[PDB]
Image 1: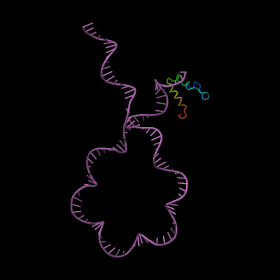
Image 2: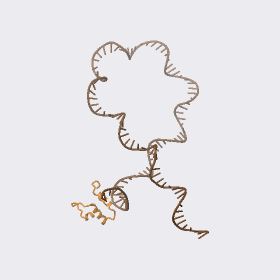
Image 3: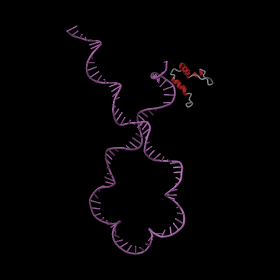
Image 4: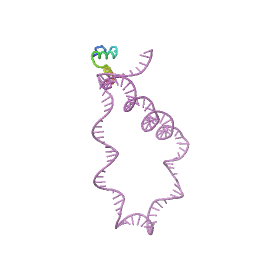
Length: 49
DNA sequence: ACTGGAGAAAGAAAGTGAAAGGAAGATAAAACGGGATTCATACACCGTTAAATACCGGTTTAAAAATCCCGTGGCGCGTTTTAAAAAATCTGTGCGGGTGATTTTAT
């Protein structure tokens, strides 16, 4: 939902991961950031999904 | 003079950094043993023949087989030990979201 709100579509330029992690932590998820980054990493590995 | 608190000295017990050394590991040089070539040379297979050996008939005789009496130790039974193998029970560990923390360099 945060990535959708940021307008980070599939046919546009990439964005830094720190910005997305900061948005998620500051607006929706009241927890740590390293776990969020690790969760984001797993959803991009071709040998995991 | 006497009392009770407080600071300083002195003494004894515990923690400490450093210690040969030795069994317990670890790592290289060496001696070994097991395949691919390369032939010359000794070995395998085929005709010929004198000679050495197998075989039959009948003795025999000395040696080995058969038989009887007995007196033992070597197997057999019952009951314990004792390792050896098997079944049962514990110990780690990694997968993914969460909580909280550490270190070294340049100017």
